[PDB]
Image (cartoon, rainbow, N blue to C red; front, side, top):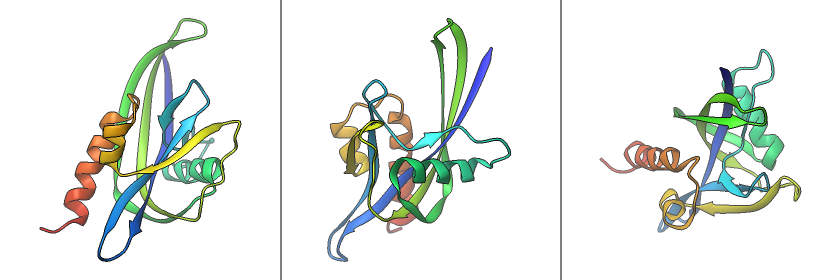
Length: 147
């Protein structure tokens, strides 16, 4: 009955050295009810999904895009809001190597945690995104690592 659409970026960087490095994503904790997610939001009218994703990233974190990977991830949810209205919601995540350091607003954001996807799977509770994180880890493993 009510449809919502959101667009976000999974922000990653590689940390370490040519000898040892780890691919980590920027996990954000939202004071909005205390749960982990990635920078995401609605598209402003006329704005492409990718532009919306880059804009939200920037607004929430001050990071900049270095490059996007050729891949998106999608999750769908259904729930009820204030007026017991039925909301089918679809969220589209891009994946991007990112530069700069984080500048979060303490009002919106409770914590910022750089973890590998496996670190995140092992250590964090994030039902909104577990599937997304699982898929992303599978993707970067075949896309970026030997074979």
